[PDB]
Every structure is written in C-alpha cells, then in structure tokens.
Amino acid sequence: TLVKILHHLEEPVIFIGALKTEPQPDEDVHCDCLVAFGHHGRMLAIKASWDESGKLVPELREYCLPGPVLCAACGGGGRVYHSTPSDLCVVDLS
Amino acid sequence: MAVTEASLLRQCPLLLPQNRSKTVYEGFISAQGRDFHLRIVLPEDLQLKNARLLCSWQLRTILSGYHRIVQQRMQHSPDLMSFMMELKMLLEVALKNRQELYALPPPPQFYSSLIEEIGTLGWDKLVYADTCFSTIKLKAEDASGREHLITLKLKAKYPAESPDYFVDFPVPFCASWTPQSSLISIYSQFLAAIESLKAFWDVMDEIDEKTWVLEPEKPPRSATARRIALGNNVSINIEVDPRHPTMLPECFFLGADHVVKPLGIKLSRNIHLWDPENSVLQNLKDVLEIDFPARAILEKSDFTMDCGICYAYQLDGTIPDQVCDNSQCGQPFHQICLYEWLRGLLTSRQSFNIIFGECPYCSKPITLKM
Amino acid sequence: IDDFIGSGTEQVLLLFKDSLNSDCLTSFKITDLGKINYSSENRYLVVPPLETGLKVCFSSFRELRQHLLLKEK
Ligand SMILES: [Zn+2]
Ligand SMILES: [Zn+2]
C-alpha cells in the first residue's frame, strides 16, 4: 500500500502452531493439521477432509479441554505438550 | 398448526420476535439434546430470497460444507417454518455423521454402582478397565486352575441394558441380563460355562502336552479341532464333542494313501475298544495300537514341509495335505497348486471330479480328489 | 522439601535424631505421601479411569455453566 477473520475463540489466545498428523531426519516437515489455543481451555483443531463431495472441505473440531492453559508447544509425530497450573499434560492428534 | 403463528412456536419454541413486525427472530434452535444460538434477520417484507442468517462460531463449525446447501435452501424455501424444519433435519444429519463428539455418563448411578458391583465380585478378579470405563475385563479360574477371561463393553446405563459379553470358549455364551442382574449374576453364568467344558479343557490340555499338535498353534479355548501329527508325513485331524470329550471323537487321516489304509482299517477294528473312563490319548494309543511323537518340531525345523509348488505353508487356510504315493518323493502339495498343475499339462487325464497325473518332482502316478 | 528424585513432583525429606550416628543424613525418610516412599495390583489398577471420569464430568459441568450464562443474556 484485506485482513480476514477465521474462527474467533470467545476467550483469549495463547498458542498458534502446526502439527504433522498422519506421520507415515529432515527439519522442515510438511504440516497436515493447524493448532491454536484459548486460555479457558478451548482448543481449535483444523484438517483437510476432501470427503463425500470429492472436494477439499476444512474439517474443524473445537475441543473444550480442562484447566486455564498457560503455555504449549509441538513435538514430533502429531503431539502437543500444554500446561495447566495443576499439571503439565500432553495431547496426541496422531 | 396450519398457520406458522402457532406451528412456528410448536416446532421452534426458542424463536422470539425482537422487532414488532415479526422480522428479526433470535434466540435458539434445538437439535439432539443441544440448543444453539441463531440471529435470523428478514427484509422489510417476508422474503427469504434476501435474508441474513448469522450464527455462533460453534454453529459455523457444525454447518461445515453445507454453507451452499443451506444458501440453496434459503432461496428455494417458501416460508421460515419450512426453513427451520430443514435446518433441524440437516443439523441432525451433520451431527449423526460427526457422531464421535457425544456421550456423558450419569455419575450418580454409574461410577459408584460399578464400584459397588465390582466390590460384590472382589478385587482379585478385575484385570482391565478402560479409562472411559466402557470396557472392563474379568478373570475366573477353572477347577483345573486355568485362567478364563471375559471382556465386557458397557453402555451409558450399565444396569438398565445388557453389557456386551465377549469370551473365547467355543459354545455360544448366553447371559440372562435383567436390569436387576449384575456383574456377579453374569460371573456365576461364566463359571457354569467353564465347568460344562471342565472335562473338555482337560482332554485338550492332555492332547496339547503329550502329542505333536500341528494345525492349531497356540490354540485358543475356542478350538474343538486338533490336527495331531504321527510319525512324519501322515496327520490325524480330531474334532471333539465338548459335552462328551472323553467319549469317541470323529477323527480321520491325512497323508500318503498307502500309509492311511492300515490305520483307518485298524481304527474300524478297534473303535469298540474305545472307553470313556480313560483319556482321549489313552484310548487312541490302544485303538490305533501306536504312540505319538513329542514335537518332531525342534529336530525337523526345516524338512521343507512346504507345498514344493508355491514353497509356502498356509496358502489361504489350506495346508500341505496332498502327498506322493512314493517312498522316494513324499513331497507334500496344496489342493489349489496340484489342481492348477495337473489341469495345465497335456498328459493329465480326469475322470469325474478327480485328476490323475504325474507328481511334479518324481513323475509317478498321483491322484487328486477335489 | 524439594524434588530430589528428578521426577518433577516435590517430596518432603525428614532427618531422625543425631543419637543414632554423629553424622548428617543417616536415618532419613523421603516421601511424596502418594506412591513415592524411600527410607533406611487391584488397589493400584482402577484410578486413572475414575479420575478421567471426574475430569469429563468437570468439562460437562463447565460447559453447562457457560450455556446457562448465554441463556440468561
Ligand atoms: Zn501351494
Ligand atoms: Zn512324487
């Protein structure tokens, strides 16, 4: 010199990243799923479906996970490590 | 009702006219014990050709790849009534496909009552309970001292409906489930099924210890047939009646037709000298006047007991059974392999559902009966 | 009190009296008050299912709370 709005979790955002779901060494891995966090423990999950019409459609979940989520990160093979002020938990998408 | 004054309320209770001219409806829609937000603005007249339909972002998630379907439905639909009938029918479809998001248990009935009924059993029994508590697995002992498991799968209401009962043993397991019946009821039924086979398991464990079992390999409790080997390159397959196991089983012989003849002939002489006081083995040894070898497995670890056409054991359930009537070849084969060999060649000559031909390895007369 | 083990979880360390030996950290007791107990299978089988049942019922509770707030609004 435009900005697009996608989903809107109602609660604040903490973490954005990506995962390699369906993991069937190289550093740049071509990520299949997309991940975002809410705080009050809304998790957003996205994937490519291409199902029932033979056309790409975005498969959304919205999970409601326990605990006020403080921080998270991604590990090898569709795994996310996140934390509640109780416990450090893990999630397998794979 | 006929009119959507009353039929609208009667079908969508949760649709409240904000504006005076009934033009903005808002509030909710019901759907599989699940109410959702809705904000459905009409134009200055009642037209759905132009209408704004905004949602919860939760609702956008569940109307994934029907955005166009419902856009069609808005322009082709007569009334708002009919639109809502369709939007409900449609949600029900979307969610019943996405049916992997649902099912909360009733905690005041379930978790406790399940802890209660497992206390009724005793804690030494339980071997597995799933983290959804949906599956559990339980243990019982025979009078012999054999472990018999039972898998259960549980519904949202365990005590109301039957839990799905899965168990190895061969006769079909029957569990008289009432809403009053419990884990202890079905456990007693399980012990009843164990003891009706108690003699049966002993006869089978006896055969499995003392004889070269061939063709169940680590047999389950479900197997009633036992392909025993005897000498080498002849076998006997044995189906036993589980209610009369010590009693005479239907038994017959595989191998070379010159070796099977005296064995069948001596079984026919000595089948009246069967006695159900002895074991199955202690009657077969005196009927057929033989011993059984103890696992010619470990010495004959590669004798190539493979088809010698395709060179595999286990082609599609079939075993190497068809052999040569020759001392110098003795080469086993399969039904499929030997048939696709003897039909392909010129020399081969078929009577009705038999092929006579030459053994591939030694070129001697070999007979195949389909 | 600290995590001496390198598990993640804190434990409590207790030193019993100097009459036993004229030496530090003889006659100790390390404990977490749960599983971990260091010093000088139907019980411990069926807890995670029950705990996850608690957490799922907690998420349902939390869900209905939010739903009701919306309804009121
Ligand atoms: Zn073959
Ligand atoms: Zn031959």
Image: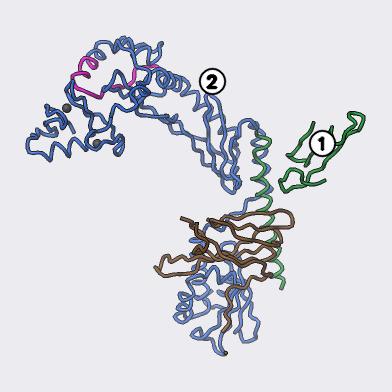
Instruction: Identify the image quadrant of residue B229.
Output: top left
| Residue pictured at 90% horizontal, 31% vertical | C22
| Circle 1 chain | C
Instruction: For label 2, count other residues whose C-alpha is less than 10 Å away and answer few (under 14), some (14-19) or many (20+).
Output: few
* Chain shown in brown: A
| Residue pictured at 71% horizontal, 53% vertical | A87
Q: Is B115 on the left or on the right of B6, as rendered? A: right
| Residue pictured at 60% horizontal, 58% vertical | A80
Percent of width and height locating residue B162: 54, 42
CB of mark 1 near ligand 1 (< 8 Å): no
**Residue identifier under label 1:** C29
The residue range painted magenta reads: B246-264
**Residue identifier under label 2:** B143
Q: Secondary structure beneath disc 1?
A: strand
Q: Secondary structure beneath disc 2?
A: loop
* Chain shown in blue: B
Query: Are dots 1 and 2 in contact, CB under 8 Å?
Result: no
Percent of width and height locating residue B255: 23, 24
- From the viewer's side, name the closer residue of B332 and C1: C1
| Circle 2 chain | B
Q: Is C48 on the left or on the right of B287, as rendered? A: right
Q: Quadrant of the C terminus of chain B?
A: top left
